[PDB]
Structure formats: C-alpha cells, structure tokens
Amino acid sequence: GFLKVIKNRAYFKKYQTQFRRRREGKTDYYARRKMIFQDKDKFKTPKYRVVVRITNKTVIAQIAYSEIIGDKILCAAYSHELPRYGVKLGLTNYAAAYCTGLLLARRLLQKLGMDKQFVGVSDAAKLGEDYTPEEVDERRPFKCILDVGLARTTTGSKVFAVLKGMCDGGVYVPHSATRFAGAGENEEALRSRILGGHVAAYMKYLSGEDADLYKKQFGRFIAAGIAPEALENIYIEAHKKIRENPAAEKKEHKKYPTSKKLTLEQRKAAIQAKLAKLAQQA
Amino acid sequence: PLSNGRNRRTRKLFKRPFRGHGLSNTSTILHTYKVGDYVTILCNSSIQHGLPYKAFHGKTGRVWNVNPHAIGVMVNKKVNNRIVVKRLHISPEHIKPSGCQKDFLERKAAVAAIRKQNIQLKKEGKPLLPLPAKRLPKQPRPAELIKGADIKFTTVAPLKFEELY
Amino acid sequence: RLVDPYVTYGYPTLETVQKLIYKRGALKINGNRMPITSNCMIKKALGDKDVVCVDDLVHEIYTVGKHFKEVNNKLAPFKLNGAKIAEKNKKIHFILGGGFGNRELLINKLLANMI
Amino acid sequence: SKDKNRSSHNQSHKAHRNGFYKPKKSAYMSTKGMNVQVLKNTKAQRKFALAKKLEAKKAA
RNA sequence: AGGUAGAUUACCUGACGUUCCCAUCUGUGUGAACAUAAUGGUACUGAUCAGGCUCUAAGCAUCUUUACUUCCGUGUUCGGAUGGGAACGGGUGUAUCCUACUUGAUAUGAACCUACC
RNA sequence: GGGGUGUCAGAAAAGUUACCACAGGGAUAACUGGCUUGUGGCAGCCAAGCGCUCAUAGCGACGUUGCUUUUUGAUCCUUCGAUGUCGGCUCUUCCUAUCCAUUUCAAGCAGAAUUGAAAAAAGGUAUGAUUGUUCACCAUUUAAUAGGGAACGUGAGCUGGGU
RNA sequence: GGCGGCACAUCUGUUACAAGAUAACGCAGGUGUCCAAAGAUGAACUCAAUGAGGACAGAAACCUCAUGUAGAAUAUAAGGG
RNA sequence: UUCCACCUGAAUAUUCCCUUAGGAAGGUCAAAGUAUUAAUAGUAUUGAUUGGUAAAGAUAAUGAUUAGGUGUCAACAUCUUGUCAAACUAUGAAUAAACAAAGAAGAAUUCUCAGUGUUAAAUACACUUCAGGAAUUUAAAUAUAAACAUACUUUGAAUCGGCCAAGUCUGGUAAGCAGGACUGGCGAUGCGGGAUGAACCGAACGUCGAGAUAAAGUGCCAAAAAGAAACAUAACGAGUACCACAAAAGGUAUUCAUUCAUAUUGACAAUAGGCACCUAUCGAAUGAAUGAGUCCUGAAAAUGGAUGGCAUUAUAAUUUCUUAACUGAUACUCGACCGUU
C-alpha cells in the first residue's frame, strides 16, 4: 500500500546521533561549555561548579570540576542524611534545600581546613537577608558556580535555597538576590520559607477546612507526631547541629544479576533449532 | 578565473566531516596548551567568529603565547622567494594538538630510562647499560636457513587467458 | 630508482673494487683531487679513521665497514672511459636490452671495458 | 593587438636560484603582543635581579 | 546493584517483542502560598496513597544501521622513461605506488570521579 | 568623521574630415600564398524501400567513412622606407572528377534514340541581344558547344567600362 | 578598428590540475542595497512533510496524536553553518 | 652609435599607473664590501598530520534515466535491472604541502633556589638567559651531500612582445588557431645524426695528439657486416620516429591458429546405373565457422620529380635474432700547452 516509510537503510546511513547525555535529555551542552571554559592562561587551575539536582525525594548537591577523563566530585551533600540532624520528614522543601546547601558549605570548608576564618551567618534572625562572603585578612573566600541543570529558574525555585545556604555557610557563590523566595514581599517572606513557614501554614489551613484532606497530604507527618508549630524550631536545631558536625560519615554490598549475555555457541544453536523445526512444520 | 574573496573555494575545504556536524568535543576546550607546544591549525567552519585564513588550514605551528580565550600560534609562510614568520591568535576551537614529535618523545623516554639506570650501576659497581641503537633504514637482510621439513612448493607459471564474457 | 634513466648500477666484485681504486682512485686533500700515489698520502687523509694502506681502503669499501661513509666520501668519483653501453640503446631499461637500470652482477662486465 | 595575459613558466626556476631565504632565529624570539600579565611578571623579575646585581657592583 | 556529574560521541542509533525493583530512580497524589500559562498538560511548589504500566537500566533476534577483519584486487587509476607499436583514436612493455563499491566473518560498548545499597 | 572621483590608487572635456598632414606597424584589417575544411564540390560502405514480380537495370531513406581547394568562412605566419588592387581582349601550358570523336562491358538494350560504367587527356569544344559584371537568362549553330589551375595565369601586354 | 558587451572596482560555484598561485569577449549567477531590529542578551518552543481522525471544509483554511537529521527557515546571488 | 683578450651572465611572475609600442616597486643578474657562522638542502627514510583530484557510487544524500516483478487501468508503495553528472557525493588514491628526527648557542641528572602572578591558600602551576647558583655524567640521538660551505650587505645594468615539445587541459568542426597547470628547451647555441629544418635524438664548445664511445648506421654516393628464420614483392608495394598524410568497406588472394562435422575398407569431386537419395570404380584428406598477420581493390588536380638520389626484389625491403663484428661528436679517458679560480 501507500506507505512511504522514512526509516529505510538509506535513512540511517546519513543519520548522525547526538551526544550521549544530550540524547538522554540530561545535559545541556550549549550552556555546559560556558561553565567549563576556564581561561587558557590559567593552566589546569580547577573551575568549581555546584551541581544542584533535585529528584522526587532527595536534593543532591555536589562540587565538581571538569576534566578530560571525566568529572571529579570534590564533595557531595545529600538530603537523606538530614534525619541524622533531626529533620525526619520533609526532605524536599525550601527548608531542607537550605540545610542541604548549608551542609555542603560547612562540610567543604572543614575538609579544606578553612572553616575557622570563614563562618558566615548563624542566627535565625539574619536568615532572610542577603549575605555574600568577603575577604578575611587577605584570603579570598572559596568560589563556586551554580549549576541548575535542566531546571527552570523561577522566582521561588528551590535551587536558590541551596545557593542561599552555601553563602550563609561561608562559601562564595556569585549571584543576585532577585530570585530567592523574596524578590517581592520582604526578607521575612524568604526567612519564613527557610523555616518551613509555607509547610506549617498548610496544615493549619488544611486542618481548618477538612480532615481527610489533611490526612491524605500529611499522612506521615501526623503519625510521626510533628505539630505544625514545631516546624520553625525543628530547623533551627538542624542548622545548629549541622555547623558543629558536617564531617560526613563512614559491610559487603549485595548484587543482583539481571539477564547476562548469550555466547556465540548458544546464539548459533538457537537459530539451528529454529531452522530445523522450520522443515518439521513444512 | 576566481574572485578575491576571503573564503573563496571552500565548498569542500570548509565543509564539516560526514556525520560530524553539530557541537565539537569537550576536550577541545579542556586541552591545556603551553608555550612551545606543537599545534595544527584546522579551521572549524561551525564557528565563524575568529576563523583563521584558509591558507593556514593543515599547517603545523608552535605555540608562542597563551591568552585568556585565544592561543598564540606561530607558523611559517612562503612568499615570492623567501619565507616569513606568521604570528596568529587562534581560539582552541580551530587548533589541535599536533602529534609530530610522538616518535621523538618516546625515544627521549627510552634514553632517559637507560641513563637513570647508569647512575644506579656505576656507583654500585655493576657494568653500565648502553644507550638504545640509532634508527636506520631497512638494511639488507642477512643469510639464513630454511627448514625442509615444514616447507611446501607451489609452481608459478603464466596463466592461460580466460575471457570474462 | 628515481634517477634510473640517467644511471646504471649493480653489485661489484672484489676484483672490480680493487682495479677501480688502484687505477682510477683519488682522494680529496686540502680541496685538491690528488690521485693515490703512496700509503703516507692515505695515512694522512684517513689516519683518524683507522685506514693507513690502500688495501685497508679496499677492505672498508668492499665489506662496508663502520667508517664507510667517512672513507667513501674522501674518494673522488672515478672518471671512467667509454664503452658499449647497451645492445639496443641507452633509452630503455637493461631488462628490455637497454642501457640504464639495475644490472645486478652484470655491471662488472661493463666496468671491465670502462676501467 | 592582444597579448598573453599571464604565465607561471620559469617562475619556480627563478625562485630557486637564490633559494627560499629562511627567517633568522631572532624572528622566532620576538615578544610583541604577548600576555599582559606574563609581560608584567617578566619585567618585575628582571628589575629585581638587575637592581640586586647592580648593587653588588656598586659596593666594590 | 542503583543514582549524580561526566569524557569517547551510533560497538552508544531505530523497529518487534521480553526481565526485575530489595534500596535508588521514575512514574504517582494535591493546588494554599513563591511561581505558571487559554489548560496544575508543561514549568512551580506541597507530599507519600498505591505501581513496576511506561520510562531508565539488562538481555533476544540468520533484525536494518554502525565499528573493526579477510576478500574484492594488485583489478580501476597513477609518478618516471623510447628513433616502443597505431593513419587516427586510444592502448603496451619496463622499474614503481595502489584506492573504492560489493560480499563473507566478528562485535552491539569500553571507561572516570562522589554517595548509597 | 562627512561632502568623490563607478575610467572605482582618484584629468575638469563634443563631432567631422572623400581637402586632410606627420612619426611609425605586417605588434594590425582590405589581395595572393600557407595550416584547417565547418560551408561548397565529388566519391564511397550498409540495406528500409521505389522500380507492375524483383533491395542492388536505374535510384537508394535512417546511419556512416573519405577525398579536393575550383565558393565562402576561421587565424593573422610573410609583405605598411608599396608585390599595381575587378572584368574583358591576346597567348601558351597543365589536371580529369570526360562534353565529342576512338576501343569496350551492362540495361526493364527488338530497331532508332538513349541510360550506367572501364581504357584513354594525343585532337576539338562556337556566333550573338541585355549587363563593367564573374554569374545569369535567352535566340541560334554544332559531333560537342565539359568542368578547373597556373600570385583568384596574364596592366614596363592592352583597355579604364566597374570599384 | 567601429557597433555590441564590461571580462575596468568587485562576490559565489565550476574550468582548476586532492598545499599555495592560477588564462580566455570560458560557463551559471550576483553588488553599488536592506535593518531600532533583521544589533545584544535571557527564557520557552521545534521546522518542511507524511499517516490517522474533526461541521461547513473540498487537492489548499483551523484543531489533535504519531513518525519526522532539518528534506523548513535564516533580507539578498551561490556555496558553506 | 667606432679597439683586443679574459671572467660571470639573464627576462616575458607579482603590485600600481589616461595603463596596453611606455613607466615605478619587485623577481632573475653583475660588480664592490664583509661575518667564524642559533647561518645548508628543488633529495630519500621513519613518525604524527592536511587535502578531496584520478577512481568509484547510482533507492548511499541532490538530480538524470531503462525496464521487470510483488501489494492495494493508472497511481502510490516495495524488491530488482540498464546507463549517467564541470557547476552530485559516502569512500578515496599516485604525485604533492607543511612538521619532528635534540642550537639561549651539544645533552642529562642531583642539590639549592628567588620576583611577580594564578590560586581558597598554596610547597601545584605560568613566565622570568629550561630566573639564577654548585656539583656529577656527557659529544648520543635516520640516510646522503655540502669550507672557494654558509649568511649576506650596498650600489646598479638589462628585462617583463616571447615561441616550441608533451603517455596534459579549456573554447572551437578543425587549424602551423586562442588561452592555461608542471617540466625541459629555442630565444642566448655551436657540434654528431634525422638528406635539407630555432625547438626532435645524442651531447653543450680554451688550442691539439692518441684512444675507446653516444644518437644512429654498415649495396654505391658514404667511413663501416657476415650469418639465420619467416610473412612481403609480377606493384611508382616496402624502406630512418617528430615528418610532411589516408578511412569505412569488400576479396574462393595468401600464411598461421582455434572450434565442429565427415574422415575406411571406404569422405569429397568425377564417371556410369536406378537435381535429392542409394550402387561400383576412383582411394586421402574433405567440408564449415571464427580470429590474427601480409597482399589487392577502395586511391581523382593542376611546371617535371622525389624511400635524399642511383638502384634492390628466396633484397640492397620488412619483423626478430646470432657473432668478445665494425664505423663515429667540439661529449668521455690519458698526455701536452694557454688563461681563470
């Protein structure tokens, strides 16, 4: 029939596949080479990026500098280790992102041994206002670069909560304070969201309207016993308990075979069985 | 009769390699060039800004200066009856690490390895090893014996002409 | 091979090498093409190359010794006589019956009529 | 009265009579238009070594 | 085993089906606020009720494609050189260099840093 | 920086001389000669057919191979301190791709008249009206009134009709 | 020579001979402009076409899904991207 | 456009001009004057590259084009088939182009080490005579050639009308036509040979003596050959390349080879008997096709004439050979003399 399929062997001879990671939809190579390109007259001096990736459950933050062999990670700070600092639930908020961002800033400075001269801000009253690290004595702050990946940068995007935590942690990340949870309203709007204000106000609103709706949205919050009013102070201790111990943490891994390949002996034998039966049916 | 345009006669010279369009490698911008290295000028038509002249395509040059975004390249140009020095500033997207001294560089390593042993043998008293032999063209082959136990004979004669139709 | 139409060459015998040097040999001394007349003239030219006699000059050339290049460069190119170059003419290869090309061991016959 | 327009005949023979004049070694060692910071580093050190050397000559 | 970042950029692609999820990833629920548009479909944010259904990843097939290997074939063509042959046209011999298409066999990825099982 | 030279490294510029003048040129045209032969002329090979039957007595389409320099082209090699530039008259000689006479063969050759072809260039091949004409077209006569070359034969041989 | 044309300043492909240079009154074409956006940057989207569907609606109107290596578009001539 | 000898010895590219019969910058060239000299290569090899020509491809991308199947007249799909591209291309040579094969002065190692700057800070890194300094070892790292080598500096002459050949190309029917890429020549060049010839072949030149040679020749002009085998030659046939001419086609003319059939007691032609057929004699080759050489026709122009001429004809022509045969240039070897370095 009238098909005219454009998939013939003549189509694939001229076909040119894209880059592998771009083919996967994970890497934007047009903006990557802008964040990789160190000045040529800086011979092999590392250029540092903050790889911020937010999954459905976990906020991943890494410090990576590019090399020809691959990308090397200087330090990583996940959000699933927040239960070690008192935050049991809500690992993907504007609040947990701030703690995940702050944890990496303190963890890296401790590893480099420069955490005594660079301390940032700590009090909760100054959580809402902008702060950029400055020169201490004559030593410049550690400088990084934000890598948001394939994430749209809105006016309240969580990827700027990770950035805000790092700056308050003592790490210099160049930025402008027009995309945090503020950029409108005032500092307290940003500061409250850093303390889970939007989550706390949700339950006290959802409970006011309905009960099954409140149970469906916050099922594990109710079971764990987390009151809506305790969110603000449960993150202050998380910020406190992070600054005094960000130094990471320490069996046999369990493997599961998946399919395994087929050798040429089995590959050739199967065709022979198929060929032999073809005459038996014929 | 041609025109005197800057990029004349580049229908095939400036065409991208087959199935080699789109973005270039990442190691192109990550390679670290240093003064004194050998490079090859390869005009990448995909980047129209700072594209070097078509006469320097394929020319091998020496890096003489490193700038924040461009790499200085110094090649030789041929003029009426003399040769002049051409100094260029080329972004890494158009140059390539030359491999002209690949054979030479490994010979230096072979000699430096032997010399390092000769300082481990003379003081300890052992006889010192000699340097590797120099390169020579293919010399005449020497005489040798061919065994008659694993040999076989095939006769060679002109072939009777057979038609292909 | 590139200069084949203008040269004929082959592999010489020891007798051919001896007669070429003894009868037509010469050396470059002080920029002068002086013929071989003494072993002192050979010792002076090639003293540092461990060649003092004409038979040492012959032996180095024939066996292609370690100091062949220095010894061979000293000898001036022999000026030979005229002889019947070919059967047909010198416009074809020796394989076709011509004059130029690789004569292998047959260059000695041509050299005999030319020395 | 038409003429012949152009010919390259006997032009390579003319060019190889007094052959291709190679540039001297001084042509490859020029440093005009180099990196500004690299030039500043070299000038700063050359002034430091020169002053020290001239001071010792002055003392004696 | 899985996830993040990659470098090589089809041995990595495309089509027909198949295998697990124990962690992770994903899909999945919701729309009050940051923020989003004609549409909570996208993007944004809040969450964990269920699911391996698609993804993703691992494998199958006389699978197109792709990458190596022999063969094609010393065949086409080519540098040097006749007072060589032919009325032309074109085509030897000599000393040399030697592709391509095609077909057949093999493979269907290798490899780097960080965390967790 | 702008105002422009488009002949675009950038003068401020209409014709005609047949009444013409000078320095020069075969660096360059008009005539012969020379290479070429598209064009012109002539000749072959094949056989679809015509020829009442019958491709080849006589023709031979569609294709295709050559010869000639008697047309016109193409070029610019010789001649620019000059090779007298059309035709006609007079005269000699040469070519055959023969018009007649001579000797032959073939026919769709009964005779007569013819047509195709071979030997053969020793002999002959005209008179006038119109036109400067070469050419042409007419009226005759003749065995026939063939085609061409010789610096497009021939101006210290003529004529000066043309240019 | 004149008449015609510009091979007179100039760009693209080819002649052109796999470095560079490069002929003809060689071939097919092009320039004396156009743009406050058609400059710069950031974000989002993916084009031409084909298949299957939806009132008028049909070969061409608009909407949806699938395939879709650019077969579209990019001021202009051609070639590159 | 006015005397002699000796030495060196060119040009027809590129840029600009009211430029095209001419000028200036520049190239080739000459003469003077230098430097111990990171300052040799029209070459080959090994190593890593660049290219897109010759070639090749033709439902591999863009176009061109001959048909045959299968699936739902045509059409559209899909599988094959024949032929193509200077302004098409996946692939892609040979020849080429530009590097490296050890010059801050011929390597390497160890110790020590400073100023700026990069940097989060650096003991990393970058440049600084491989900053600098001192010890130890050391002349090694493809081939070939090169000290009247190499690198030049200054001043300046002439010249930019070119022409020819081709195992090359474009326009043209073609041209001893017009214009180009690479090289070699004539111009500027004589000598030996092609009879005669600017370019072809050998080979380039101070004055000579002797010898082997080159291209090419050895019946006479004309120095120098004898032998062997064949297809030629009953004809102005053949006879020294460039070169001075010949085609398509036809022949029961001739030589060799291949394939096929009949050749025996009997194949063909002939004779006799009942044009085909069968009988007897006749007794050895016969018939058919094709290919490769030579020959004949095809083959007609003007002064009388040109293998150079005379002449040859199992050559004194042609094709190939054999013989430690020969002849011959101003080129090669040896010797003598003149001049330059």
Image (cartoon, coloured by chain):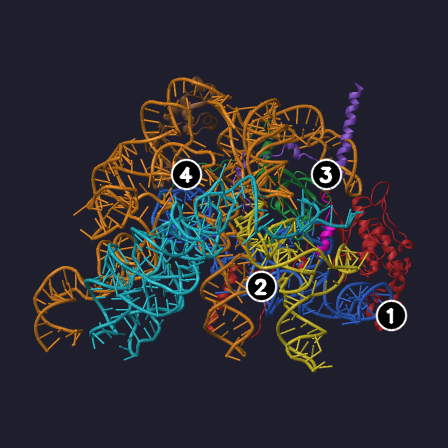
Chain colours: A red, B green, C brown, D purple, E blue, F cyan, G yellow, H orange
Q: Amino acid at mark 4?
A: Pro
As drawn, the label of residue D34 is 3
Q: Nearer the viewer, residue B26 or H77?
A: H77
Q: CA distance from mark 2 to mark 1?
A: 57 Å
Q: Which residue is mark 2?
A: A11
Labels 3, 4: front one: 4
* Residue H40 image position (x, y, % from top left): 56, 32
Residue C75 part of the magenta-drawn span: no
In screen coordinates, is A78 left or right of H142? Answer: right
Mark 4–mark 2 distance (CA, rounded to whole Å): 54 Å
Give the class, few, some or many, for how many residues have Cα within 10 Å of label 3's Cα (few <14, many ≥20): some
Q: Quadrant of residue E33?
A: bottom right
Is label 1 in contact with label 4 (beta carbons under 8 Å)?
Answer: no
Residue at image coords 54%, 36%: D14
Q: CA distance from mark 1 to mark 4?
A: 104 Å
Disc 4 crowd, CA 10 A, few/some/many (<14, 14-19, 20+): some
Residue tagged 1: A206
